[PDB]
Image (cartoon, rainbow, N blue to C red; front, side, top):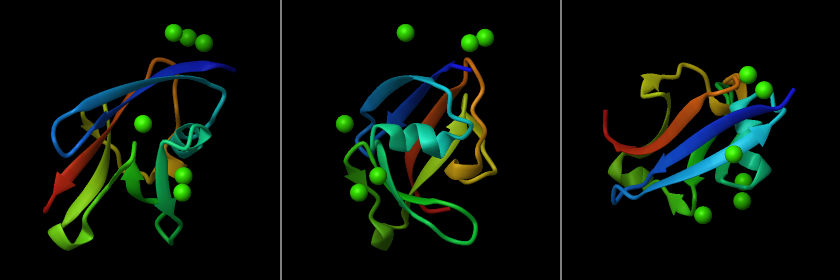
Length: 97
Ligand SMILES: [Ca+2]
Ligand SMILES: [Ca+2]
Ligand SMILES: [Ca+2]
Ligand SMILES: [Ca+2]
Ligand SMILES: [Ca+2]
Ligand SMILES: [Ca+2]
């Protein structure tokens, strides 16, 4: 079935870009890659997202893309994150830990 979701990208300079998807995808990674909104690499814990909406995290400055769902922590890699109708996800560029 078709689910209606939003993905908001919070860039390094605080620019927020909001993307709406109408999707039958089971998982968030499929949704993100449907429009090539992210680039990531496979690995043993799932997708490691390096670039979102044409912004690449600088590994050397401890930057990384973080997935949240209505601001709440998401425990799964994007390719293992189930999508529900009405979901709002965020991808935020974070620095450090
Ligand atoms: Ca529906
Ligand atoms: Ca709409
Ligand atoms: Ca891609
Ligand atoms: Ca690519
Ligand atoms: Ca873009
Ligand atoms: Ca519904």
